Image (tube, rainbow, N blue to C red):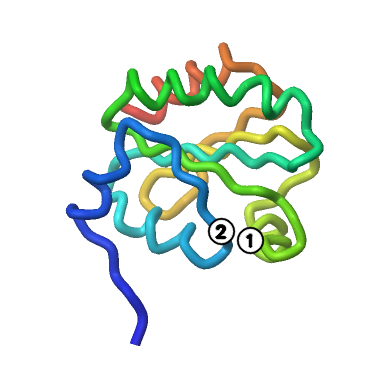
Amino acid sequence: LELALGTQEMEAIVGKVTEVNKDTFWPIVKAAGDKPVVLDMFTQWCGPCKAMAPKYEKLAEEYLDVIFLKLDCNQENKTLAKELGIRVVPTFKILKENSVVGEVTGAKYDKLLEAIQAARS
């Protein structure tokens, strides 16, 4: 018996940035409907990653019809990471309907904002 997420849970996380793990990532993406999901893949030793954190949170406050998540690419999440295909940090993955539809590498907040606008159409 596993857990299923619904409107209740999605409504509770919009407007914020939520950190997920290899066990809570998909249950959230699957409950997302047609709302785009953005995933910030970082590491604890990643400088540009921490520096981008406040901008990412700003984006999450501006776009309430997009779900912003973050994943620490460590040992416990090695699986999910490899499965999403990552070569560098930071990496942003945009998903829509259980599939990756975009990717931004590096702290290119400008290109990220473009991809987010694109996903919303």
Name the kind of residue labelled 1 in the image: Leu
Q: Which residue in the rendered view is the most extreme toward the top?
A: 110
Instruction: Establish if 65 lies above or below 37.
Output: above
| Residue at screen point 36% across, 80% down | 2
| Residue at screen point 44% across, 18% down | 58
Give SS at disc 2.
loop
| Residue 116 picture location, percent across and down | 44, 25
Give SS at disc 1.
helix
Q: Residues within 10 Å of mark 1 (few under 14, many from 20)?
A: some
Front residue of 23/87: it is 23
Residue for badge 1: 80
Instruction: Establish if 54 lies above or below 64.
Output: above
| Residue at screen point 47% across, 51% down | 99
Residue for badge 2: 21
The mark closer to the camera, 2 or 1, is 2
Marks 2 and 1 close (CB-CB < 8 Å): yes
How far apart, in angstroms, are the residues tagged by discs 2 and 1?
A: 8 Å
Q: Residues within 10 Å of mark 2 (few under 14, many from 20)?
A: some
| Residue 81 picture location, percent across and down | 68, 55
Q: Which mark is residue 30?
A: none
